[PDB]
Image 1 (tube, rainbow, N blue to C red):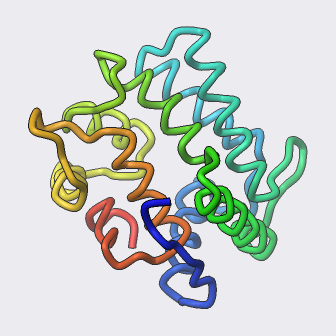
Image 2: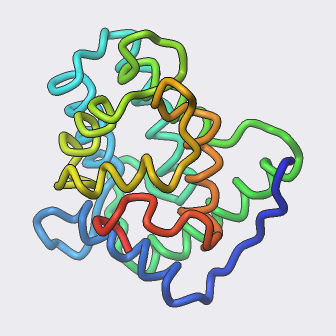
Length: 191
């Protein structure tokens, strides 16, 4: 492993980051969300907004399923906030253990599936316009300014593209650890 990455689950900013995403995913404010809703949203984006082929959409669905499944979410089950954050601690712990052992993480698997769809050239890297297209379809980022901040925070290659290796590292830090190097990865869109 190129980094020594550790959890910080009692940091109110960690908890808060995931509460933000919980509230953003709970579009109708039910106080709970299901795996059914998560995989619906994921496939809706890639198939109906981003042009995914059937095989590409299925690969992506599988990776989203396993990601949220790692946080304890299940088909036909409604997950409330207390269960969600409990599951998220397990997910992060498991991911960081795989990382420390140089084994593929669920976030890498998902990234590789998503980048196959989003990168016009299928070479594992995306342009700013492609990042804007994905994030604004998903709604996780709403403004171009915030999408631009992502390219400031990450190490960009000489052609001005964000590669999956770099985005995986940044996401490990941003979602699992509170690495201060990854602050503002989504600009002002996600605290």
